[PDB]
Image (spheres, grey):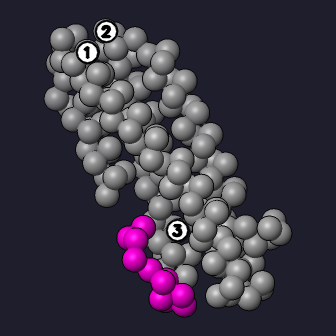
Amino acid sequence: FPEEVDVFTAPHWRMKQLVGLYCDKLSKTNFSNNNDFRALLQSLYATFKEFKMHEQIENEYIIGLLQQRSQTIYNVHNKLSEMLSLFEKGLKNVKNEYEQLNYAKQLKERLEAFTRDFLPHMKEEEEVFQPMLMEYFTYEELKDIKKKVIAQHC
């Protein structure tokens, strides 16, 4: 698929880069240490804010359009909002090492589940929405769209 009409690849290269960064931080993080703990949550909150902007950009510049033209919408492209709330909880409601370590176990559980769903969600957009975009829009329309999408991401 021509680079100039690919509306997922570059944003997703950034999102996967962010997944890699938080997985790395997660596994090197000392949850018994309060500073290490908060720094981790702070990184995670910023990261997940960018994920939310990304999904919003998709909704506003790509998905809403594709769904009006194909009318083949049934799945509703929430998750991120619950993850951000989780993080806030850790940054405001955790006082000592006992709470930190109980929290960590839950954080890890929820991030693993998030990650296991987020990668396939992205692959479905590239494998399914991209090709649909080909049949319902012209090549220049798609170029315009990618233009608007990169502007919002970058």
Q: Amino acid at mark 1?
A: Leu
Quadrant in which the N terminus is drawn: bottom right
Lateral position of residue 1 relative to residue 49, left or right: right
Q: Main secondary structure of the magenta part?
A: loop
Lateral position of residue 51 relative to residue 5, left or right: left
Residue range in magenta is 67-77
Q: Which residue is pictured at 65% across the width and 79% down the height?
A: 133
- For label 1, the residue is 101
- For label 2, the residue is 32
Among numbered discs 3 and 1, the one appearing first in the sequence: 3
Q: Which residue is pictured at 26% across the width and 44% down the height?
A: 85
Structural distance between the alpha carbons of marks 1 and 2 = 7 Å
Structural distance between the alpha carbons of marks 3 and 2 = 38 Å
- For label 3, the residue is 58
Quadrant in which the C terminus is drawn: bottom right
Mark 2 residue crowding within 10 angstroms, few (<14) / some (14–19) / many (20+): some
Structural distance between the alpha carbons of marks 3 and 1 = 36 Å
- Residue nearest the observer in this picture, 97 or 74: 74
| Secondary structure state at the residue bearing disc 3 | helix
Is the residue under label 2 in contact with that under label 1 (CB below 8 Å)?
Answer: yes
Lateral position of residue 115 relative to residue 41, left or right: right
Residue 50, position as x, y percentages in the image: 49, 51
